Image 1: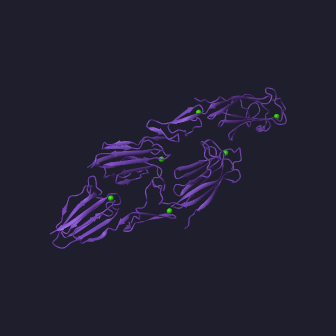
Image 2: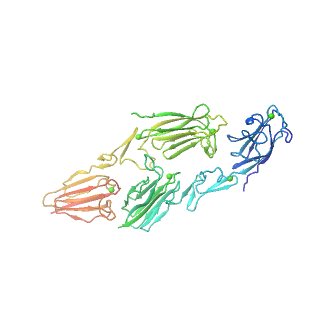
Image 3: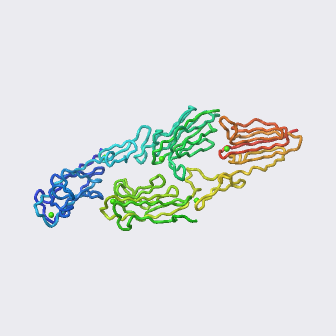
Length: 278
Length: 278
Ligand SMILES: [Ca+2]
Ligand SMILES: [Ca+2]
Ligand SMILES: [Ca+2]
Ligand SMILES: [Ca+2]
Ligand SMILES: [Ca+2]
Ligand SMILES: [Ca+2]
């Protein structure tokens, strides 16, 4: 219900299209709305040529960086003329500076430049392996939004996808149980809780199977990702490393398994096969 | 004691407090002794600001985790400056990494950081984790040690408190007898021994009376906690499970009850009322 305002304009050297004079200094600060960057190009460029544009120049800077230093008419080995190149602001702001020195041996016409704001694509551009979203990144005008696959919920940090893996209440007495996505990497910032609740007088036995991969610390044990098992009379765990933990035999009919994950890592996780006797 | 690295120290960007240069890379690995962690903070911080600190940064890592990525002077929406924040190592080690890219358009002054070792308090958990001691936990500089309540003795594992429940010699003809702390959970790694010595020609009768709770096995009987009874003419037990066992009638004037517990469990235990006839 609220939309960005357009931002666009035209910049010229003093007196354009007539020849620019000596000892002139101009600067324009251009600012796009949040989520936008600026796009600038030159329809006309004809300045005094000099080594590294020491005499006359047009300087484009953005944020903390110098985007370009331009002079002459056609780009050389150590100088740059803009040609049909396009220049982009870093962030929403862009400064344009024009300077002429004490003399022009020829009648130089200066420059005509045009600029326009365009939406930043936070999902595709400024992207290496670093996607700002855990699952789905949605670009829109002036921003972006994150969403998650089914069976997840967006964390409060608005980027991480937390599994909905609590609430599983098993009553079938022989069965399997697992970390999310296994054997794919288990999700970040998740709190899983699995409850085996069956008839009284029965005793359960739990078995880890196949592969095991939980984030470990060099000299500490399991401070990051914590996998623990709980009978109403006793506690077991936490299990880490990359070796399948030994069998466990419970006295109780009701058992609770909890799996907690922290903000980082791509570890595969765990399987558990539980059986039964009297 | 003595350690190769000092209890306190100072790290600065190359050339501090003068402007740092381009294409610079530094890394310091700081390591405290076991039982200590490292605490690091910044007295001065002024780096080039960039989206996600891609240009210049200080990265604090510990173990496998990145504690922080820092740039700028004051923290923004997607960037972090340390301010007066304190950073803590996970375990005794902590790595500091400094990097600068190809240019500095302003005189960025870099950073001054200080670190100090501090004792880990193994006794004071956030207590979402377990307590390392059975009874009393004592913290000291560089370590901790355990102790027990009166009537107990510290087990060889230096953490578990074993009850002193041997030595009870009953001569009274009618009476009660019990697992330690009943009806509170009976202690771990304890070996209790109760001796009933009565006049010749008399016969004792034993009765479980209130609650009965001893660690049971799925398909076996009593391999963890073992409660056994011994007359000079017979042996009874071991008794486990969680149902009050039937009455027992001894021929002997002499009875010895032995109760053994394992390293884990919170089971309540047992009472026994014994009487006598001719
Ligand atoms: Ca000139
Ligand atoms: Ca956008
Ligand atoms: Ca993790
Ligand atoms: Ca830099
Ligand atoms: Ca300590
Ligand atoms: Ca026990």
